Image (cartoon, rainbow over all chains, first blue to last red; front, side):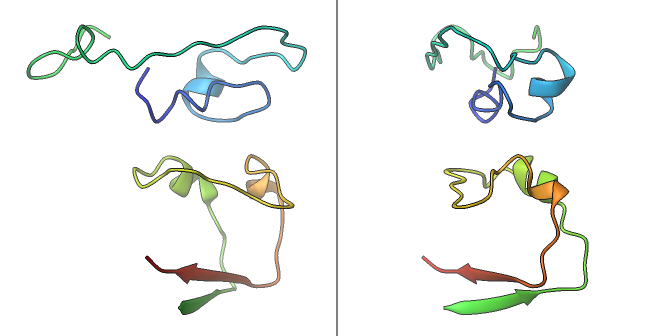
Length: 50
Length: 49
């Protein structure tokens, strides 16, 4: 997911991707780990697979 | 500062939330996800560098 909408995916947080794809429940005991992977995910002239 | 008065209008914070200048949206007293569900008398905005 693009870095603007990484913060959207959270329990009790509303958004476009956060609401229209999957919510996180309010009793979520768990972890979220992120990494900015520009080496593989970013492609020349756009990555249109996703 | 340039204090701008905001009144007599419908405030759509989803436009700001989907906007590209969007970083460190900190809030005191109000949860940022419930700002579309409230009413205010006047809203004062201060813009600076």
